[PDB]
Amino acid sequence: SVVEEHGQLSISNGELVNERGEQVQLKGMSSHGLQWYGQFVNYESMKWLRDDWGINVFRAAMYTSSGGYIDDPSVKEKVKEAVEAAIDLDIYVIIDWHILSDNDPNIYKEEAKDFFDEMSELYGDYPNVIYEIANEPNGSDVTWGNQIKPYAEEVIPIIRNNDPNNIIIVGTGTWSQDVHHAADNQLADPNVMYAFHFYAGTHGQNLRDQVDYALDQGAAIFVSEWGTSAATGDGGVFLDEAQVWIDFMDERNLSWANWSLTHKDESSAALMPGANPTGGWTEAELSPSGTFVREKIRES
Ligand SMILES: O=[N+]([O-])c1ccc(O[C@@H]2O[C@H](CO)[C@@H](O[C@@H]3O[C@H](CO)[C@@H](O)[C@H](O)[C@H]3O)[C@H](O)[C@H]2F)c([N+](=O)[O-])c1
Image 1 (spheres, rainbow, N blue to C red):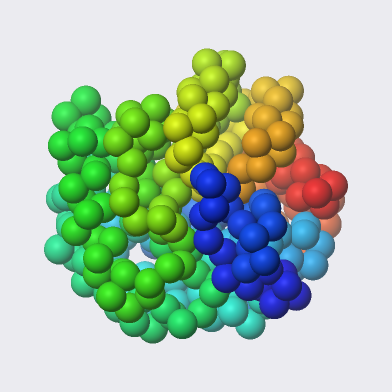
Image 2 (cartoon, rainbow, N blue to C red):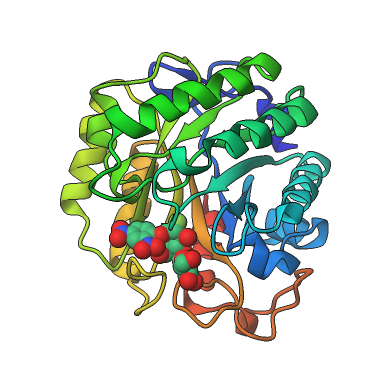
């Protein structure tokens, strides 16, 4: 009864709060690309995550390029499937317009406006939905002030015409690490959060201090993607540094989604090769990363 209990989420003094104004922290999993590992996104696997891991949020990672939505728009129906399951399971859900190689969110802004118009029209009267309008803006030529903020200022109005106050997570520069620039030039909408993403393979002490700087400007931060691996999503599992970030996020009441729910042979993948796509995973079907993430959510 997560959604029944906390209901409408909003931002108050830079903090995510429930409909009674109490601080709330969401912890869950992100899918991998829906064009590749969509079979792991379904009511049964999400229910298993809710019941056995304790998740209270699920992130649907709809890549735009890399064979995603722009090339084959059918993947938007898998996002709808995930939203409907979240509604049925009474958990929160993030709709992620998962830009990456298409590094400037303006490249597909017309399609983004059409997609968010459709999703907000369909689901704008449910409290479960969180819109993430540009996963990871990246590149030296893509800045908050010149590219990202103006993009958000075109897409947010589209959403707001159908859904006036569900949370919107807006990506930041340098693969959603540059929360410092965003916090110094914040968007006007009162229910916006800025995305901050990390990988435990990178020594993170300055990045933690940067998140703190942003929080100190009154900006709300959602860690909508993080991994136990290196920044490529592979290269080793770094559980000591991941624990430091877990403790940091708890102290700052930061919500998060781990990357990712797939059996792909890479360190950040939570599942091993024989894991059933509909859940019920034994200890051996979880990777070293999945075992750790499951423990962190169960402990919460
Ligand atoms: O340098 N960084 O800080 C940084 C941070 C984040 C990041 O990218 C992000 O974080 C992971 C790990 O890099 C990416 O997932 C990886 O996407 C690859 C390309 O689709 C897949 O082949 C790989 O299986 C998958 O795990 C997510 O799409 C992307 F949001 C990347 N990146 O993709 O290069 C770089």
